[PDB]
Image (cartoon, coloured by chain):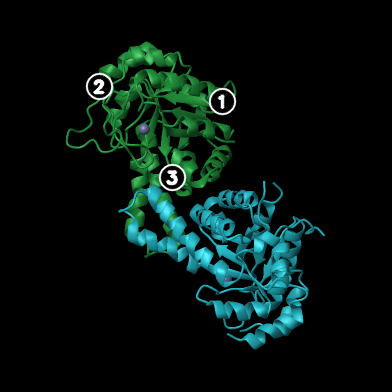
Chain colours: A cyan, B green
Amino acid sequence: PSLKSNRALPLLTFARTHSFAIPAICVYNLEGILAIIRAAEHKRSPAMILLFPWAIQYADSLLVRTAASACRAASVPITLHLDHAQDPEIIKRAADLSRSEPGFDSIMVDMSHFSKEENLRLTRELVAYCNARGIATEAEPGVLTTPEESEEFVATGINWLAPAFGNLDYERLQRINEAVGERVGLVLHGADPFTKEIFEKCIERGVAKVNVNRAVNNEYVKVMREKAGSLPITRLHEEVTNAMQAAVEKIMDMIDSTGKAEFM
Amino acid sequence: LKSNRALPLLTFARTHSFAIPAICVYNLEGILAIIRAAEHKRSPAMILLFPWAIQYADSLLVRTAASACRAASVPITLHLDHAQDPEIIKRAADLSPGFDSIMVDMSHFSKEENLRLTRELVAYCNARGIATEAEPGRIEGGEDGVQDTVDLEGVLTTPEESEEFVATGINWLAPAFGNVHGNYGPRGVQLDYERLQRINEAVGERVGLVLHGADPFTKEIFEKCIERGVAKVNVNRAVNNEYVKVMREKAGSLPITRLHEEVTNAMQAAVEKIMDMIDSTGKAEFM
Ligand SMILES: [Zn+2]
Ligand SMILES: [Zn+2]
């Protein structure tokens, strides 16, 4: 209800009902933001741009605000997610950007590194903090994720859940899905090396959001390793962005997000 | 223009014998390097973007930089450097939080065409709250983001051409007085300081003077220029070569996060040295 106008939620619910997954791309820079936005507009695909707490450590609100207004100006649904936020203070600080100027649409409240009772308790409290500001939330039931553990995390108020199942244990996956896939969206982590077939089986069994980092960002690293000092700076920027954009477009085709924005 | 944010900086710098560091950047690392350097050293600054920044990222770098400027605890404004195409100038000027100032650089055209286009483009910018810089001559050379002058001759600035440009309503002038964009080569830096003072004497009280091609300059050269009216010093390679060196040596060897940190630190250190050299260090206290 405080989430009634949240832009991030329709993406996963739509993906789940239309048997595809949203590409959720971790980026560290403006070149990454551009690559995602170009890929998505070009493949008529929805997307998410994901930032780590480091983006705020490093640039205060600047990467956040820029990514936010870039996705909102986009011609396909693109929203902004804080990935793997493991400190309560940085979650609240990120969430505070929404009491302006757009900030995050969703935050992964990742308390998985805490003891499970303290994980549960913190998650609940930070989720309530983000929801008060209009912000959707994802959590990790972090030893693998049982269907029982998943239901405990549903109770905290998360919107999406990031199960541990070898990422592979597909039997474990659909059991999680049958138990909780009606109350929360499912999020796949460690997707960087996966193939179409793995993505297909993950999607059939509930995945509506696929996190990617190295598969895209390694393209940025390859160009700089190979071309820095040899290409002018402007050209390096163009080349890293093209390389990253191409990598995002592949993922969009692998997870059937290509074309889907037409119907959203 | 009464409410223009860039104008006071050069005014203040001129009356207090220093220059504003005007640092060209291509990326968020450079934007962060400038804000940090400027806040650390308590110095005003300007962030310079090339037309390439709009060509490449539409309004993204412009918006990121303009916003960083506003949020800074020292005076920092945003300048379009070397805009050499009337169409791009209007496109940039239509953006306005966009640019506080724009360089209407028509120096590639004949003198009379340069004056003609500069006059009308200044009108267009002024209508939109935007201060302007023009080049009453032709500096030779190219940089990444700044076109070559191949097949064009150098044109040194006279007081008379300077006077002609003051009537266009520009705020700042970039004189050609022996400075060169890019590498000076074996002949070294050979500036005509006499020409410069002659310019300053003729128009200095009516317009601010802007130093281009300053990358390899020393403190003593800076001091000579500032004593002759230079209130804005443009820098590029001095700063962005640090990004290149760090990437050249370390990409593939450090996490991307540390890569971004290291280029920004290295660029920040290069900016800080300029600030000291041109005596802008500490000046934000009285602004
Ligand atoms: Zn992850
Ligand atoms: Zn220049």
**Residue lying at 43% horizontally and 63% vertically, measured from the top left:** A219
Tell which tag, 1 or 3, sits nearer the viewer. 3
Residue at image mark 1: B4
Say whether mark 2 is within 8 Å of ligand 2: no
Q: Residue furthest bottom?
A: A171
Q: Which residue type does callout 3 highlight?
A: Tyr
Picture quarter with the N terminus of chain B = top right
The total of numbered circles placed on residues is 3
Residue A157 pos. (x, y %): 77, 69
Find disc 2 in the rendering and name its residue: B192
Q: Report whether mark 3 lies on the same chain as mark 2.
A: yes
Name which of mark 1 and mark 3 comes first in the sequence: 1
**Closer to the eye: label 3 or 2:** 3
Residue corresponding to mark 3: B26
- Amino acid on which the number 1 mark rests in the picture: Asn
**Residue at 75% of width from left, 68% of height from top?**
A124
Mark positioned earlier in the residue sequence (3 or 2): 3
Q: Chain of mark 3?
A: B
